Length: 86
Length: 97
Image 1 (tube, rainbow over the protein chains, first blue to last red):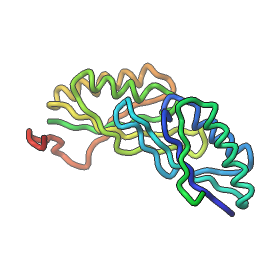
Image 2: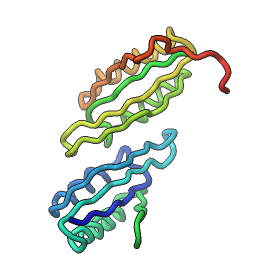
Image 3: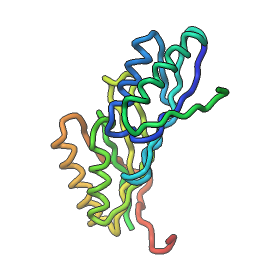
């Protein structure tokens, strides 16, 4: 099984970024674990979430990744950060 | 300086609940610090947040907690509760900036 960790930075709180991300991951046969979650220090700053995505194999997982990038685009004010060797 | 710990439970994310809790505490002259945050296994499960509430004294913090208690009673997706500390004395004196 292959897994990669991604991070969502930005307006995580009142958006559907996370549910949408979670639905996508599961929709394609993957699973996730939220490894870190830090809320925006004041009700002003960017929260972030480190999500661990888990798959059968690297091509599988990456196919999910790429779709997760596409979601990042549409939903406004959320940045995706790569943690590992891209 | 007094502190009590509270916990929100339910649909923390995709709510405005958090910014509302924070706003209310700040409006009333307290400060808060988010201590823990746990997400459920599927978005249909409940998450929870532990938040420490800090005011000038117990009387006043109790005022805040009661406002926060009424907030949770209004919003249906979430319940609010207080946590008893494993420590008796929850007061801090002035200093520590």
